[PDB]
Length: 306
Ligand SMILES: Nc1nc2c(ncn2[C@@H]2O[C@H](COP(=O)(O)OP(=O)(O)O)[C@@H](O)[C@H]2O)c(=O)[nH]1
Ligand SMILES: C#Cc1cnc2sc(COc3ccc(F)c(C(N)=O)c3F)nc2c1
Ligand SMILES: [Ca+2]
Image (cartoon, rainbow, N blue to C red; front, side, top):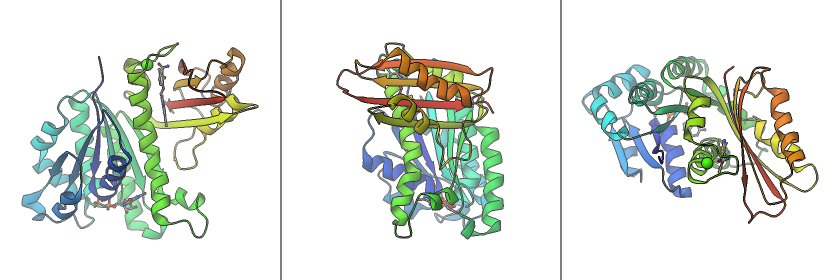
C-alpha cells in the first residue's frame, strides 16, 4: 500500500496555495486546480485543471457569491469525481469568504469523502479589513466545510498580522500561511514513504484524522540543550491556527532524531504534548532514527478531537 495523495485548490486563494506548492516542488502528490474563472485557471501549472460552472458564469469567477460557487461545482460534479479517482487522501485548500471557494469547496470535499478518501480541509478566514459580509460568508463556508470533511484546519488571515513587522511583504506573509498546508502534506508523504523504528503508517493517520472535527498539524525543529522540549513546544504552537492543542483527544506524534535520540528526551517531548491534550487522548507515538542527522531533533504532531 502506497497511499495516493491529492491536493485540490478551489477558487483564487486555494489555487494560489497550489501554485506556490507546485513552484516549491512536491514529489508523489497530485495537484488539482478548480475554479470558475477560466483566465486564472489557464495560468495554473497544475496537471489537472477543472473549470467549473461554465454554463453558469460564462468562464468568469463567482463574483464573491457562494451560491454561484456551489451551483458551479454541482454543474461540474462528474468532472470533479473523475479528477479525484484513485485518491486515498485529499487536501481541499480554499479561501473562505469569496464565491468559488466558499460555495464549491464543500461540494468538492463531500465528493472526495464519499469516494472514501481521507478528506482534510485547509482553509483561510478573511482579514477583518475585508469587512463583515466577507466574514459572515466565510463562517457559513467553514460550517459547510466542517460537515463535508473528515478534519478541518482553519487559518484566520488576521493571524498573519501577528507575525509581520510593518514592512514584511504581503507575499511573504502569504507564504507563511501556505506553509501550513505544505508542511502537512509533506509530512504525510514522508510518513508513508519512510519506515520508522516505531513505525506509523497511513492507517494511523486515518485513525487520528477520519471523522474527527477540527485539527492541528505542526512541526518543530531544535538542537542543543533542551532540544526535545523546544521542538515539541514549537510543534504544538499555533500562531496561525484557529484550533489550539488544548483538549485534543487524538494525537499522532513522531520524533525524528539522529543516533543520539535518547529515551529520556522522547519522554520529555511526549509529556509536553500530553500535558496539553485531553486526559483520555488516543496518542499514537512514532520514532525515526535518521543517522544523517547530528544534533537536530524534529517533533511533529497531528492533533484532533476537541
Ligand atoms: N492567505 C491568503 N488568503 C487569500 C489569498 N487569496 C485570497 N485569500 C482570502 O480568500 C478569500 C476568498 O478569495 P478568493 O479565494 O480569491 O475567492 P473565490 O475565488 O471567489 O473563492 C479572500 O477574501 C481572502 O481572505 C492568498 O493568496 N492567501
Ligand atoms: C505540520 C506537520 C506535520 C504533522 N505530522 C507529521 S508526521 C511527519 C512525518 O512522520 C514520520 C516520518 C517518517 C517515519 F518513518 C515516521 C514513522 N514513525 O514511521 C513518521 F511518523 N511529518 C509531519 C508534519
Ligand atoms: Ca512510516
